[PDB]
Amino acid sequence: APDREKALELAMAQIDKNFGKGSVMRLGEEVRQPISVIPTGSISLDVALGIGGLPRGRVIEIYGPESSGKTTVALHAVANAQAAGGIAAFIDAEHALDPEYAKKLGVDTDSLLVSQPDTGEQALEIADMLVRSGALDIIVIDSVAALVPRAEIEGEMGDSHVGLQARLMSQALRKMTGALNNSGTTAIFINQLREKIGVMFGSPETTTGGKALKFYASVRLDVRRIETLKDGTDAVGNRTRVKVVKNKVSPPFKQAEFDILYGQGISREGSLIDMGVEHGFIRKSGSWFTYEGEQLGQGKENARKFLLENTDVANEIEKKIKEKLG
């Protein structure tokens, strides 16, 4: 009771000191303030990070099977970082990006830097100096599994005696991190995979590069698709679930879900309905959503419709959901 809580709180103190920001931390803390934070679009995922958005000046890794929604976030994370006089850079190595879409999210493509490395070392060296500049305030290495070494991509082997794509990543991230912090340029890395089977086995290892990325990232996000959608017709989109499996700026293991419409991507509107009920700020009168008095409609997408008609009631519902959490 006495000397205990006393010796502990003290001990941890002696820890964070010679060990980064919050090395140790109880899963039920309040967290301080990393101010610099990029809205991830989805608010659900925002409070999830505890800090409300991606911690600026750090390395983020969004990993998950295909069709999940990794970039959608990343992109948004850019659409926001941008709509604030920010400069974004997109180190593409998958040659898989669709402006039309990234435009409907809020990215200023025309003003978006987008390189296309021919080798791994290249993709990373670029991001390095393209970081020192203190200009960029967010870069997005698209596809870690794609950062193939000059070697394997130069016939001379595919491996033979190495761990290159691993030795590679490590080397980079290393001198790549110290520089990120200074320039305060948060860096997102997209990881590619294939989903579960009830209980995970698979390859938490890595696409031989992410091994290091694990220890260097300050936040890691497990973006898995949970279930598709419908509303009379066929399907307007996927609902996705993100499990923040690591976090050195707030408590980890938090959850967050939200809708990705095949059209506009994230569904702010609907993202409110969900957190609207979970926070009582809106109620259900039997599949008939209603916000104190006036009903929104029968069915999430219907209330989404109505919520998508008038910005006011929305900004209001938003207004409250945010004050009940900070």
Image: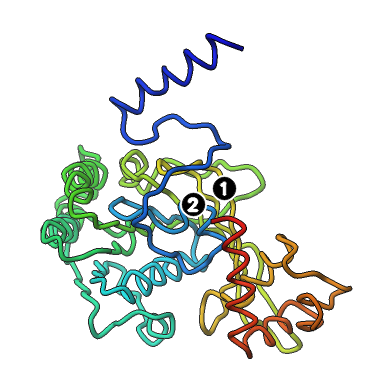
- 141 relative to 76, above or below: above
What x and y, as percent, mark residue 65?
A: 50, 59
Residue kind at label 2, given as amino acid type: Leu
- 17 relative to 96, above or below: above
Q: How many marks?
A: 2
Decide which of 304, 60 is in the foreground and name it: 304
What x and y, as percent, mark residue 263?
A: 53, 85
Q: Residue furthest top?
A: 3
At x 29%, y 82%, the residue is 109
- The answer to whether 158 appears left or right of 295 in the picture is left
What x and y, as percent, mark residue 234?
A: 69, 85
Q: Quadrant of the N terminus?
A: top right
3D distance between C-alphas at marks 2 and 1: 7 Å
Reading the image, the residue beneath label 1 is 254
- The answer to whether 104 appears left or right of 199 in the picture is left
Q: Earlier in the sequence, mark 2 or mark 1?
A: 2
**Image quadrant in which you'd find residue 321:** bottom right
Q: For mark 1, give the secondary structure.
A: strand
- 20 relative to 70, above or below: above
Q: CB of mark 2 within 8 Å of CB of mark 1?
A: yes
What x and y, as percent, mark residue 81?
A: 33, 69
- The answer to whether 264 appears left or right of 296 in the picture is left
Reading the image, the residue beneath label 2 is 49
Residue kind at label 1, given as amino acid type: Lys
